[PDB]
Image (tube, rainbow over all chains, first blue to last red; front, side, top):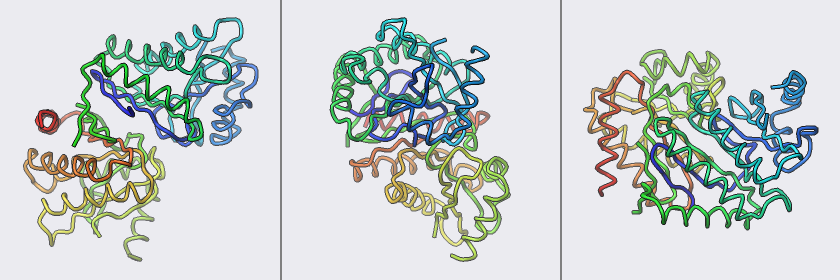
Length: 186
Length: 176
């Protein structure tokens, strides 16, 4: 209920702060017009510092798009993948496609570990169970399709959000019932 | 090359330890000289020379593991495994692994990357070093089931044989 392995991919569920993560890539969630708002966005901006914002605006104005990439500044990561929640598209669709785009960028950069927050869960954005359903659909699809790329994928739930943590645990549990899984016990 | 046992994930990885991203990256050193060895050299180059200043400060002031910050590594801490010559090398490995995983709980560490301590300098048969390393990781998983940990073993891409020993060892343990 906290970690499984499928082919060349490890998937972990973690209670903690995304902005205090150590990974190749940490994943932000933002309004494209304003990245100073939201639990994740706020925490990642505070932690990384204000120069991450300068770069964001430079790369936006230049026009780099569901995912925009910056460096990590004061995060313990190399890159940040800022997921851009454009209002013009249905929120389950943005999630689906943004997840695909995040994992494809992983292969494009020999990224070996990437940490996501509970994307989509937001507030009245997407039913907790659906967001987890979708997140796991993408991670598993990638694992089947990209078996030669070793990758650790974390979902970091904020310690207070016990219900989101529960949805995610519960979702993994179901998926394992339906999979080989290199999981053991001692 | 990856399995999960209780609340612990264990991965076997081809790459550079010094280019790792973890809470903790694990060095291997001669205590009186940390500029020698593949691992030691790579970690010193990457982290830079201030990691050496701190090493000497912490050593002189005052033990199988000495802890520094990570400087230019993508880590919070470095656990320098000190290979004191007065003790058998299989013993240092065993106890230094134990002490590294204990420090993980002490410092609330969620991921730690180890090179294959004792497969190089100290001569130990690659199979034995793997046997021992997996002994400790599994024991920790049983004994410390409430502490989530990711543990990586990072073999340099050239040594297919050490990677092979390590793969092969994990494979057996899965059967058990």
